Image (cartoon, coloured by chain):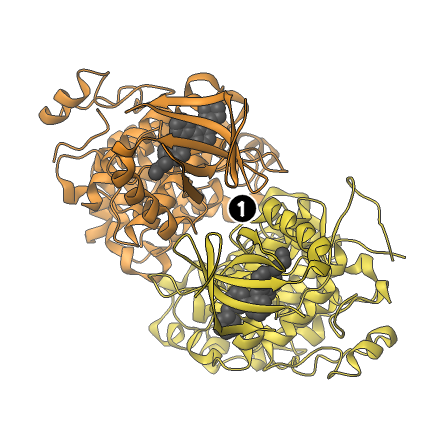
Chain colours: A orange, B yellow
Amino acid sequence: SVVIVGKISFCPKDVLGHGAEGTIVYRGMFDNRDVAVKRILPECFSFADREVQLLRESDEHPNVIRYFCTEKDRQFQYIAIELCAATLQEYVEQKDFAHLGLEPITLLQQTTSGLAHLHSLNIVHRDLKPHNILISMPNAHGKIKAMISDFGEGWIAPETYTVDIFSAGCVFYYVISEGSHPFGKSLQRQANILLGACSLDCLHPEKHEDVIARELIEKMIAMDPQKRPSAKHVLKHPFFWSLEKQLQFFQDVSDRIEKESLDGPIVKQLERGGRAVVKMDWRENITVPLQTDLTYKGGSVRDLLRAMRNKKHHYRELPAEVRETLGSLPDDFVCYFTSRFPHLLAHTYRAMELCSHERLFQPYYF
Amino acid sequence: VVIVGKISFCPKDVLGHGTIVYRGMFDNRDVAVKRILPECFSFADREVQLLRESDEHPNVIRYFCTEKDRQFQYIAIELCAATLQEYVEQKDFAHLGLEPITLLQQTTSGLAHLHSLNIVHRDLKPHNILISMPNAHGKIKAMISDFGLCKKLAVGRHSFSRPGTEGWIAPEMLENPTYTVDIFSAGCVFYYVISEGSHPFGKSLQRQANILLGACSLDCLHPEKHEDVIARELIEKMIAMDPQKRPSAKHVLKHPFFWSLEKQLQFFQDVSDRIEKESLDGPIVKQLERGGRAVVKMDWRENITVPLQTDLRKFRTYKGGSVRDLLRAMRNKKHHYRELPAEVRETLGSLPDDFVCYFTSRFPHLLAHTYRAMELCSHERLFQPYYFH
Ligand SMILES: COC(=O)Nc1cccc2c(Oc3ncccc3-c3ccnc(N[C@H]4CCCNC4)n3)c(C)ccc12
Ligand SMILES: COC(=O)Nc1cccc2c(Oc3ncccc3-c3ccnc(N[C@H]4CCCNC4)n3)c(C)ccc12
């Protein structure tokens, strides 16, 4: 009814999962801690001890699963792990995102940070997928966090560190798509990967968020392994940025290109493909009161950014008619433009990639 | 090689000392082992459960396990490089820079993790703050220890009770015990870290008495420097005898003491743009120009470099005894940095670090007076990351 094996004790009725060569995972207890216990046969001992040593070497991190201890009996070996509420899989297939808002994005920042923690220790994750991503129990505030397991099927790369980026880029789309997969469904995930067939049609260029998600993932699931962002690179991507940071970025860019010549390498880079970004004439795409409150060129990103810089600067000096439509600072403010000009931040970010080494534009790139 | 269960230790390797602490091993993990007599079980099992309840956090010491012997009880703890105390008495701060400041954010964050669980730390001193082993990068982190003196407040709020060691203790125990007690002890550790070992309430054998008396001395922090003031103002609030005048654990994390020069600057822009339409009799500026003459050294146009003084276009109409116009200068100088001549950019400094530093070196009370005076627009989301939540 309830086995006690050293400091690991569990009740078989409370079963959490069942897999591979006769392995069952229970809800047990270690030193009065709620833990998930996995019993394994001698066929998996040599493999088990290999994963375990890595846990000891990387459990220091929050976004890596915490290993406690292991004990062996006459027949089995039991492995103690921090009890977690659910997987990223159970979290997407059952839990509604309308009352979470900011939670899913946080899980990728966490997952990516923990995945980076392995890279700092010259470790390579190979089987990274939502069934392995673990969701922590609710804290006192009510917040949660993500943790990785299994440090070495559709999440596999066709081909090093760049491999984990491929798996992750598919996991990002998985959380965003509420269950879909960039390379199609099972029994075609492996094949389409070999071909290079991707489809992120859950992300349309008619919205700001979708584009910013595509640019990142396109790089990640890319055939060219060297064309994939490092783990810490992903974290300084606009995908995780706040509205305060989006706006202050536009401003740093706007003040930066004030003296740069129109024949400048940057402005050409910036105005290159601008017509689609500004929809030919941005004076027409915006509200009447603002349109009536405005040398700003329609096909100009630079003048568009110039308007945004100076209008915020003198926001308190603006009419009540405009302040209402422009939106309160800074959230609805930048949203007023990104909603209307979605490729802007993506285009701006990559076009200002030249000035990445500049100290004013380090916290955006690294 | 002594072996008691899965925890094994070698007696020759003693880390500290009727409790003695050894260097042992748990499941091929490097751990610090403490041996206790049966007399200290009641305190230990109470201590361990708190570690069990809060070791999830990085800035809290990780408890692994304990084993029982014929005579003793052995407790396994994550091995740490050194204490904050050993860290101050031996390590030079000139080649670390922000590491010490980070140890306080870590320490403060871990203390908040306990406060999130309605816990009060009572025996807090640098000997309890532990320094993690170097990571692959070479970096470290701080972790709290010793929860023998820790109060698990039953429910929600209120205050209960009202003792080990001396000089780091709050007066409320010497009946008003709360989370803010940890702030007093913690606030004193800052001065210990900022200094080369010094303490706001004097040296040992009089730290205890002067606390009762209220004698504090932050003479290691003079208003002739920027950091000292921003540190003094914070610590002054933290070590305040008046317990309700003490910052919460989470507020301290949002104090200018931990801000970067980018945030000092990015804050000034938000402030200057905010007072753009404000009347001279405006409620915000009245608080701001209140005691401003001393902040700007009466006339700031005189205190700054020559090229800038000659680069201050007269059309803006800048008054000397006016702080807002000075902030306007920094705002207007920041906006058009690329439009300014190369002559000024050299003295003003490259953006944004040397730029804001150019003023703080000359105006240490600036960021302090502004932040303290700009508490009014705190509820506005443009002024959330500077104050609360
Ligand atoms: C030697 O290597 C190992 O033994 N590695 C591992 C040991 C232990 C677990 C491990 C583990 O975790 C689980 N594996 C299978 C079923 C359930 C859990 C599990 C673990 C912790 N919490 C929960 N929570 C439940 C709550 C109810 C809904 N389902 C999730 N499940 C993974 C993914 C990988 C390696 C593990
Ligand atoms: C639950 O009750 C307990 O038994 N609690 C505790 C158990 C075990 C340790 C505990 C502990 O730890 C130490 N206590 C005294 C001396 C040294 C260490 C110690 C621990 C880990 N690393 C190091 N590093 C050395 C490296 C060489 C230089 N000196 C520092 N020191 C504290 C502070 C509190 C409670 C402990």
Q: Indicate the secondary structure of the residue bearing disc 1.
A: loop
Residue B269 higher or lower than A311, as above or below:
below
Q: Which of A254 and A218 is in front in this view?
A: A218
Residue A90 higher or lower than B39, as above or below:
above
Which x, y percent locates residue A328? 57, 36
Give the quarter of the figure containing the N terminus of chain B.
Answer: bottom left
Q: Is residue B254 visible?
A: no
Give the quarter of the figure containing the C terminus of chain B.
Answer: top right
Count of number-bearing discs = 1
Left or right: A87, with B371 as reference point = left
- Ligand 1 position by quadrant: top left
Label 1 C-beta lies within 8 Å of the nearest ligand 1 atom = no
Q: Which of A356 and B170 is in front in this view?
A: B170
Q: Which of B162 and B146 is in front in this view?
A: B146
Q: Is residue A79 visible?
A: yes
Query: Residue tagged by mark 1?
Result: B56
Residue A327 picture quarter: top right
Residue at left offset 71%, top offset 56%: B43
Residue B37 picture quarter: bottom right
The subunit letter for the residue under badge 1 reads B
Which x, y percent locates residue A194? 10, 26
Which x, y percent locates residue A57? 36, 52
Which x, y percent locates residue A237? 34, 43
Check the image and name the residue furthest to the right: B175
Residue A121 higher or lower than A19, as above or below:
below
> Hey, what amino acid is under mark 1?
Glu
Left or right: B144, with A85 as reference point = right
